[PDB]
Amino acid sequence: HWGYGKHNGPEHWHKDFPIAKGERQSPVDIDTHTAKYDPSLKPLSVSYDQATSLRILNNGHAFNVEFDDSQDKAVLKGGPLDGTYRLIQFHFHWGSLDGQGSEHTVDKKKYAAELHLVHWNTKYGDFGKAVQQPDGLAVLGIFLKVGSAKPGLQKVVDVLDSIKTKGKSADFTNFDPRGLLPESLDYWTYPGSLTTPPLLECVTWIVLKEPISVSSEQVLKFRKLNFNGEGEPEELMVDNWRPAQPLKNRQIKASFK
Ligand SMILES: NS(=O)(=O)c1ccc(NC(=O)C[C@]23C[C@H]4C[C@H](C[C@H](C4)C2)C3)cc1
Ligand SMILES: [Zn+2]
């Protein structure tokens, strides 16, 4: 099956998932000088005060913090979006070294990691339906650089010992995802895709301009996770990122100048 190794990594994905070579694939490089300021872009509306986290899961590719998305509890609105998008999960992609790990790049610059807060358009009823629509998902992407610790990340870091291997999950209630946001909500936006198989072209990407900082110890703990299941040979979960894909017939818009 697919993964991030030499023999099953991003260069191989197109054989099982031909959409890998499609017209709106993610991630992309964000060329800041070519991005277009769009003065009609609305401020983002992040409403996470009623967020209900449930569980954290190692799925063999990353770890997901899952939320109750059966009511409008944590929602994203505004920006380039019309309608209401419910938070279903967040996860990260990260590197084996501080100089790589993000999926999006900014003027070819790679960050140490990238956080994805995944939301789906409530007009489609459930997540499985939403991924089949060109405006089905909105993913809020946030870059991580190594520097000071991010206090709101620590509870996530603390529980990783409990989900070291593929298929492990742990209860993860009462987590506040607002503690993962930077100060500014200035963003770039473009139409794209899931960045792992099935690579469906269903995502409005909203990538924040301001990275958050996390400590060396925090990212080091990400790198102690395993891609493998318990009792299988140990493969460190690092470099679980897809490289930038061609922009093709797309323009990246900026909410700021
Ligand atoms: N990195 S990213 O934010 O772009 C991202 C987000 C999410 C996924 N995958 C999933 O949620 C799993 C899932 C498996 C099948 C097929 C679809 C729909 C349903 C049933 C859920 C996808 C992959 C990448
Ligand atoms: Zn992701």
Image (tube, grey):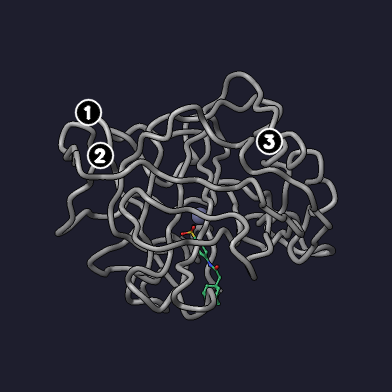
Q: CA distance from mark 1 to mark 3?
A: 30 Å
**Residue drawn at point x = 61 percent, y = 58 percent:** 89
**Residue drawn at point x = 30 percent, y = 35 percent:** 108
Q: Is mark 1 within 8 Å of ligand 1?
A: no
Give the x, y percent position of residue 41. 26, 45
Tag 2 near tag 1, CB within 8 Å: yes
Q: Provide the residue designation for mark 3.
A: 153
- Vertical comparison of 114 with 8: above or below: above
- Judge depth for marks 2 and 3 and give the one in front: 2
> Residue type at mark 1?
Lys
- Mark sitting on residue 257: 1
Left or right of 247? Residue 79 is right
Q: Is residue 131 visible?
A: yes
- In the rendered structure, which disc, 2 or 3, sits on the residue that comes first in sequence? 3
Give the x, y percent position of residue 173. 80, 53
Q: CA distance from mark 2 to mark 1?
A: 7 Å
Left or right of 242? Residue 112 is right
Tag 1 near tag 3, CB within 8 Å: no
Q: Is residue 35 visible?
A: no
